[PDB]
């Protein structure tokens, strides 16, 4: 089942309200034709270069960063071009990305919220229509709708009374979510 961690600061927040604010706070790194600059808005794989157990990206607007965890693959120019596919197990949201492939992994200095046991697995053949692609591209581009939908579905699958409109505290009472230390 989905496992959620949250800083005690966000106990009284709904998952939906947190993700709507986080998307806007991270914003859009503008990873699009004519707009890409290396080490500004590419992100990075661990270990890479085009595959990793992690894909991580820093905001160009704020200190926000995310880490996507699983078994992830990027196609670059190869058909289907510019597809992120594979297994997405976890999304970690917070501030101040540290480490990388040379440190044995990426870390957030301030992890606010994470979603684990997502169980998402998108094959290469789905291209940019894959759920993994849409979930992570949404985080890159200031629209967490796809992530919100997947979390909503996973919560309702544990118990139909749960949704992204539940507070983190309500999800903790339901045995899904776990409080972590405040920054």
Image: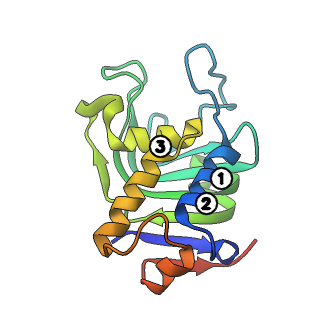
Position of residue 66 relative to residue 172, above or below, is above
Question: Is disc 2 placed on a helix, strand or loop?
Answer: helix
Pointer 2: what residue?
18
Residue picked out by circle 3: 136
Identify the mark nearer the N-term, 1 or 3: 1
Q: Which residue is mark 1?
A: 21
For label 1, the SS is helix
At a point 41% along the width and 39% down the height, the residue shown is 134
Q: How far separated are the C-alphas under marks 3 and 2?
A: 17 Å
Q: Residue at x 59, y 80 (%)?
A: 179
Residue nearer the viewer, 167 or 119: 167
Mark number displayed over residue 126:
none
Depth check, front residue: 107 or 135? 135
Figure disc tally: 3
Tell whether label 3 touches label 1 (CB within 8 Å): no
Q: Position of residue 158 (x, y in %)?
A: 31, 74
Residue pictured at 68% horizontal, 52% vertical: 97
Q: Which quadrant of the figure has residue 141? A: top right
- Most extreme residue toward the top, as rendered? 34
Q: Nearer the viewer, mark 3 or mark 2?
A: 2
Instruction: Answer left or right for 113 relative to 59.
Output: left
- The C terminus lies in which quarter of the figure? bottom right
| Residue that extends furthest to the bottom in the rendered view of this protein | 173
Label 3 secondary element: helix
Label pair 3/2, CB-CB below 8 angstroms: no
Question: Badge 2 local density, few (<14 within 10 Å), some, or many (20+)?
Answer: some
The image quarter containing residue 79 is top left
Residue 116 position within the rendered picture, expressed as x and y whole percent measured from the top left = 43, 65
Picture coordinates of residue 71, whole percent (x, y): 37, 49
83 w.r.t. 140: above or below: above
2 and 1 marks in contact (CB < 8 Å)? yes
């Amino acid at each position: 089942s989905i496992s959620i961690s949250y800083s005690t600061t966000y106990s009284g927040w709904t998952v939906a309200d947190y993700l709507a604010d986080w998307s806007a706070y991270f914003g859009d790194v503008n990873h699009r034709p004519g707009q890409v600059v290396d080490g500004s808005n590419t992100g990075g794989f661990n270990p890479g270069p085009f595959d990793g157990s992690q894909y991580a990206l820093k905001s160009t607007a704020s200190d926000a960063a995310f880490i996507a965890g699983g078994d992830l693959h990027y196609t670059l120019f190869s058909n289907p071009s510019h597809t992120l596919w594979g297994k997405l197990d976890s999304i970690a949201l917070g501030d101040t990305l540290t480490g990388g492939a040379s440190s044995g992994g990426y870390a957030l200095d301030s992890q606010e919220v994470s979603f684990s046991n997502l169980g998402l697995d998108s094959p290469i053949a789905q291209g940019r229509d894959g759920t993994v692609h849409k979930v992570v591209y949404g985080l890159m581009s200031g629209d967490s709708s796809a992530l919100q939908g997947q979390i909503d579905a996973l919560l309702k699958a544990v118990d139909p009374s749960l949704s992204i409109n539940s507070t983190f505290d309500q999800l903790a009472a339901a045995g899904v979510a776990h409080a972590t230390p405040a920054a």
